[PDB]
Length: 217
Length: 210
Length: 198
Ligand SMILES: *[C@@H]1O[C@H](CO[C@@H]2O[C@@H](C)[C@@H](O)[C@@H](O)[C@@H]2O)[C@@H](O[C@@H]2O[C@H](CO)[C@@H](O[C@@H]3O[C@H](CO)[C@@H](O)[C@H](O)[C@@H]3O)[C@H](O)[C@H]2NC(C)=O)[C@H](O)[C@H]1NC(C)=O
Image (cartoon, rainbow over all chains, first blue to last red; front, top):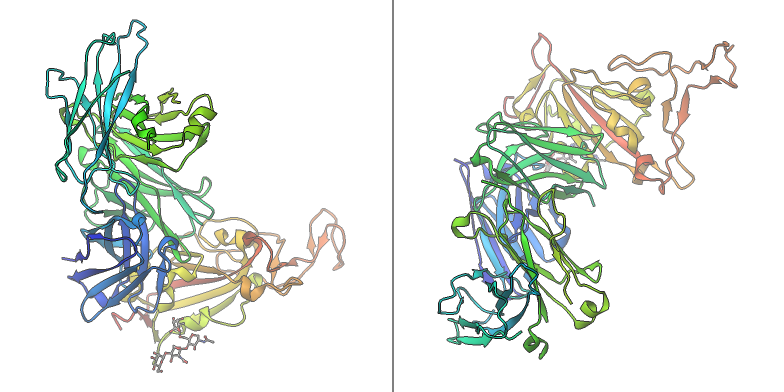
């Protein structure tokens, strides 16, 4: 049972340093080459580095060339990735993998379950900005309308109207750093003739700052 | 540097066969061994093909791979499609001191197909008081959408994007994307379009902001 | 230390011209293969009829190491079933090849500013080489219907032509050092074994 269990940091400040560990069990670690591979949320797989069974051969992806530094300790059955000068684009699940067959490492064989490294920060609540509507009803009667919630940490900011309108196509948030924001859409097929009022009730949580705005065309 | 480029998405019906392509650029794909890795949603990657066209023990013979040096491409082929095959598929090799992964191809085992509907409008003049734009997408299957944000008619890198989640019991998908902008570009060109490409049929899917 | 001399095949100072490709028989030794472990120092690495990850637990009657220099866009021809000037007239691998092909860019060794012209290849031949055949003769090649009488001229060509390896060539025209290991299994005891069944 070849097993790789990465252990290491999670949330870290940009410009700091973090030390990943990979614990190998179920095979002669000293005779295999090891890879580091990351997968930022939403993005695909990207190779970090590789180290020979000896430690004598080390190669790095260009995007980590100087900051990151691979190493191993065959007595401790452990692979290490030293990443100093951490930047925000290095936020990913970090996988550790062994090379196919002994010694050779042109391919990866067994992968670990990864550790998620988040680089960022301070707990704070958001503001809210209205989205103004448009329609120009041409036998369609489709007037899309909503609100925004910018720079909120963390989930789950509640958004609705607390009333009878139950036709809101609410959405989710892109966790990026480079914003954190929500949105929701509401539809009024009459294209309200300056009459129907749409309050947009938006409560926070990590700052206790519920806010509301009125969407005026 | 040597590059591996895969299609963003592909999809077929259960029992059918699909083929994921992996075409190299700035180097020959046939030079070094090509691997194929499978990553199920949320899981860790697993190996499915090694050394161009070998299967590890446990990988069903439904999985096959080959090289085509004429087109400079490797091709994974999965027969008798099953819902368990739904995953991101990454081809991999190396050029000298650099190990390269393809961008990855999300495979969706076909529920009906539905093109997405797009909404965009950033009139939060309360935000111009201190502006980030909004391009909303909803009700699409399969869940793989690629959106290009074009300042005037030229792309931007300030564009942020979500991970295409599944909206509740609809089983379809809906994503959102935002970008930080200056008033100038939306005034500059007649539009400030935001275009969505879903399946082979991406007729429009782009609103004209200002 | 009856260790097989594979590293000396790879780190040799001088490499043969492809038309006179060098063959070193490897016998009666324990196979190292550690030079193959560093895939990053090679431009192409492929085995045939065997996986590289199995070499350390296998035994063979003989190993032959063939080595030579060719230019970049010609390395694809060092593979079973290929055609071209190298595969037809210089070095031909059999269809049932069992072994590995290794090559790397050697521009920093085999190209000179005025152009290196010491590396030759055969341009013409009355017929294709059979697998693992070598042809070092220099008879004038009769390209037309009129015979040559050992004299060069129009349609009467010296059969060896010279590479022009200049450090500023494109990689397809830069020199590449190639090593071809073929693993031979006869109905006789093995003399070369990996370190895991010595
Ligand atoms: C050409 O290559 C030979 C063979 O050694 C090779 O070294 C690597 C570069 C790979 O190509 C391998 O496939 C292969 O083993 C060189 O000769 C040998 O070099 C090694 C390392 O320098 C020597 O090993 C050492 O042995 C001593 C005790 O003998 C130990 O203390 C060391 O820890 C180490 O294990 C080996 O003895 C040596 N063999 C001989 C016969 O000299 C050779 O130097 C090289 N030539 C050039 C010009 O680079």
